[PDB]
Image (spheres, helix red, strand yellow):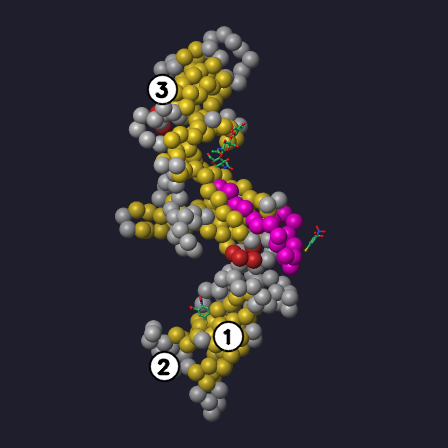
Amino acid sequence: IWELKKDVYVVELDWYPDAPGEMVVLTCDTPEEDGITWTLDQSSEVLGSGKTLTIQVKEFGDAGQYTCHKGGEVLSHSLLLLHKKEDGIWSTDILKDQKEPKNKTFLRCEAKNYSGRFTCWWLTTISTDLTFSVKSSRGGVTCGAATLSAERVRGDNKEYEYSVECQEDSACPAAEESLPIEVMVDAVHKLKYENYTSSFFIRDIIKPDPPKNLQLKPLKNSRQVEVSWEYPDTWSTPHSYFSLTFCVQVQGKSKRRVFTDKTSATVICRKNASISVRAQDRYYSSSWSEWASVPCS
Ligand SMILES: *[C@@H]1O[C@H](CO)[C@@H](O[C@@H]2O[C@H](CO)[C@@H](O[C@@H]3O[C@H](CO)[C@@H](O)[C@H](O)[C@@H]3O)[C@H](O)[C@H]2NC(C)=O)[C@H](O)[C@H]1NC(C)=O
Ligand SMILES: *Sc1ccc([N+](=O)[O-])c(C(=O)O)c1
Ligand SMILES: *Sc1ccc([N+](=O)[O-])c(C(=O)O)c1
């Protein structure tokens, strides 16, 4: 048993029927010795008396808000959450595996520039009685609260998307990163305690916003057209240091590529086709932005 936060404790259990469990001794945080009584959750049943209470924690029934009373008053609480360890590996019932980069990815982090600011997201089937706590650091990072940012429909069930925004306290955009950023997330659903983590350098999780103000300018006595665009607003300043490279593609009806560092390109439009442009950090091979498109008709 260990303290997660003030008056909240986690008990690590090997998860299988009739597991021995853990002998847990709760001590009431009161200096009074007389008339102490003990209760679990909403039940009125006295489990014992005295300053100490011993329980065998073997299942969720033994977990909960243990309360010590004196003269009808509440003296202290000891909230017991469990951390199930099924077949040698900690449970992951709360968050869905996003499966995107390479399996067992529950936390997905992304940055839009080098400001030291980033966003992490996760998905759950659970709609309430669910709390999250996010902490982050390099190897001084401040994170806001995990907020509900999207609600979707996946088959029979519902999918809730949570996101958190963090900022490195004393960022330095242009500097080389020697130590990666670490995100730690605690997940509590009723009485189930879970643990999640992610390690990355800002440079690797970068994905700029798409090129903006895409324009198509036809040319006289030419089959070709000129497409032009601008750097996105959220991208890092100045562009001279933090430059972007681009890729142009003509997306037609068929489903069976030009690279440039410029904000313009000359291409051939065709009926029913669209011109598409993506961006990548010129100097680091991170994620390509989402497409910005302009149609040919
Ligand atoms: C994510 O979950 C894991 C596993 O439940 C957490 O690891 C556990 O962390 C606690 C807190 O530091 C460790 O407890 C300490 O154990 C020593 C004796 O071994 C004791 O002297 C300390 O007072 C305290 O009780 C616990 O051993 C450790 N479990 C394992 C198997 O390593 C981990 O901390 C969680 N991540 C978080 C909340 O950041
Ligand atoms: S890029 C950068 C900004 C601020 C500071 N700072 O003096 O705290 C540094 C730095 O000197 O570490 C770098
Ligand atoms: S023009 C272009 C650049 C990058 C990528 N990409 O996302 O790997 C594509 C593409 O394959 O869609 C096209």
Q: In the picture, which quadrant includes the C terminus?
A: bottom left
Residue 97: % across, % down: 39, 48
Residue at (58, 66) in percent of width and height: 283
C-alpha span from label 2 to label 1: 23 Å
| Left or right of 169, for residue 112 | left
Residue 288: % across, % down: 48, 64
Report the residue marked by disc 3: 43
For the residue pair 251 and 137, the one nearer the viewer reads as 137
Q: Amino acid at mark 2?
A: Lys
Say whether residue 243 is visible.
yes
Residue at the outermost front position: 88
Q: Element under label 1? A: strand
Residue at (30, 28) in percent of width and height: 17
Q: Amino acid at mark 1?
A: Phe
Tell me, for residue 271, which label it has, or none: 2
Determine whether label 3 and label 1 are within 8 Å by CB: no
Tell me, for residue 52, which label it has, or none: none
Q: What secondary structure do most residues of the magenta stretch adopt? A: loop
Q: Give the mark, 2 or 3, whose residue is nearer the N terminus.
A: 3
Report the residue marked by disc 1: 259
Task: Classify mark 1: residues with Cα within 10 Å, few (<14), some (14-19) or many (20+).
Answer: some
| Position of 273 relative to 50 (above/below) | below
Q: Amino acid at mark 3?
A: Ser
Q: Give the mark, 2 or 1, whose residue is nearer the N terminus.
A: 1
Task: Classify mark 2: residues with Cα within 10 Å, few (<14), some (14-19) or many (20+).
Answer: few
Q: Is mark 1 within 8 Å of ligand 3?
A: yes
Residue 274: % across, % down: 40, 75
Q: Element under label 3? A: loop
